[PDB]
Structure formats: structure tokens, C-alpha cells
Image (tube, rainbow, N blue to C red):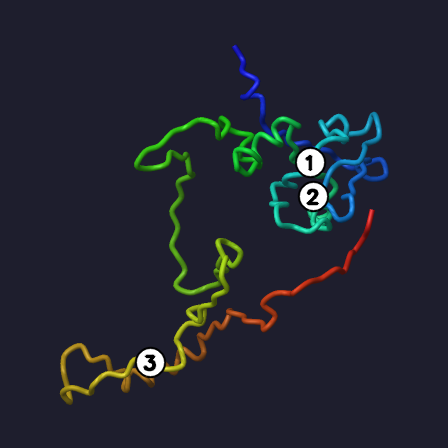
Amino acid sequence: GIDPFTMLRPRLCTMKKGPSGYGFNLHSDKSKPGQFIRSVDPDSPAEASGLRAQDRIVEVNGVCMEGKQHGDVVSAIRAGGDETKLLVVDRETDEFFKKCRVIPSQEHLNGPLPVPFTNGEIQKENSREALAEAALESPRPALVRSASSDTSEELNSQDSPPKQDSTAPSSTSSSDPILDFNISLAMAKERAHQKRSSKRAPQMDWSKKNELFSNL
């Protein structure tokens, strides 16, 4: 009682390098985008892993290859180390997700296909439970490629802007003063305990780079 639709799912091919590299050929056509397997030597770990001359790379070591250059695929392998893990889909599966308007990945390996239709007030998820004290101030990069669509920027990144919000002096003295005049001297000690661990370089990003470390 097995449907041909449920078998339509990715497969993570894991192959370790030993005999002069992994032993597989990868190279995109030319003007056509995407990366495909040209061929693989027989009796090789790549072949045993499940890699075929008709497979498409969707993710490497669990990284997103979508929107990445063709040089990114090899880069991911090098970053992985002496071993690599390539995610591929079946011929029917590949087109199955494209017409379904979905994004295959390692997450699809565990759990049922996206074909099921379900809904509710909250989405079910078995997330891990952990508790920790949040830092008062420290590094914390934000998203700049998610739903970016239009161009925008925020200066909220820098703590304590150029000018504060001035308010009327009110009475000469009152309870709970917002005046740090006297406390100003105390703030002097903070100088020694300074911790400018933050960093802001002018090179936000590069328009385009093609160093091409190596070309198979």
C-alpha cells in the first residue's frame, strides 16, 4: 500500500574523499544556470553514495545553494573538509517540487512530504527547550537578504545616537530625577571597564568578486 507520490523525496549523498579526490565530475553548461553531475567514475564512493549522472545539487553539507554562484558549490565542499554531503532529488521529485512551488532541503528528509494539507491556530513543532541569560550588549548580526525586496537601512544598529531627547528642566529639584550631573562623575569609572567589542567596517558587501581559487 505504497503510493508513487510519497517516494518523491530528496536523498543526502555522503561520500568521503580518498583516491585523488571524491572521484566525480561537476560543471555547469555555460549560459544555463544551475549545477548538474556530468559523470562519475565507477566503483567510486560518489557512485555508492547514490550520486548519478542525472542528479541536481540542491544543498551541500546543509547549506543553501539557491541564489549562489556556480563557484559556491565547490567552495562548500572545500569548507566541509575531507568529506562532503550532497543533496539531490529524483527526476520526478525535482519537477514535483517546482510545480508545487516548494524548496527541497535536508528538512524534507525527516517527516512527511509538503503535499499534506493541514491548518490550525499554531504550527506544530518539536523545538528544543533551553534557558539562558541574554547578554546586555554584544554582537548580533541581522538579516539583509530576507524579504529584502526594496533597499533600506537602519541606524538603530549603533547604541546611543548623536543626540538625546531634550526635555523641560521643570522644578529645580524633584523625586526620581533624570539628571546624571552628579552621577556623571561615577560614569567616569565605566571608562576603565569599557568594552568596545563592537565593530563597523565600511565594506558592507562586494558588488561582484571572481577570485576563482580553483576551476575543475
User: How far across and down, in percent of the image, does residue 7 sit?
Assistant: 58, 21
Residue 95 sits above or below residue 78 on the image: above
Q: Please report contact status of discs 2 and 1: CB closer than 8 Å, yes or no.
A: yes
User: How far across and down, in percent of the image, does residue 103 sit?
Assistant: 55, 38
User: Badge 1 is on which residue?
Assistant: 56
- Residue 178 is left or right of residue 77, and the answer is left
Q: Secondary structure at mark 1?
A: loop
Q: Secondary structure at mark 2?
A: loop
Precedes in sequence: disc 2 or disc 1: 2
In the image, 176 versus 111, the foreground residue is 111
Q: Amino acid at mark 2?
A: Gly
Tell me if mark 3 has few (under 14), some (14-19) or many (20+) residues whose alpha carbon lies within 10 angstroms of its own: few
User: Badge 3 is on which residue?
Assistant: 164
User: Badge 2 is on which residue?
Assistant: 34
- The number of numbered discs placed on residues in the rendered structure image is 3
- Residue 61 is left or right of residue 144, and the answer is right
Residue visible at 42% across and 65% down in the picture: 137
Q: CA distance from mark 3 to mark 1?
A: 55 Å
Q: Amino acid at mark 1?
A: Arg
User: How far across and down, in percent of the image, does residue 130 sit?
Assistant: 40, 43
Precedes in sequence: disc 2 or disc 3: 2
In the image, 134 versus 101, the foreground residue is 101
In the image, 195 versus 3, the foreground residue is 3
Q: Please report contact status of discs 2 and 3: CB closer than 8 Å, yes or no.
A: no
Residue visible at 65% across and 65% down in the picture: 207
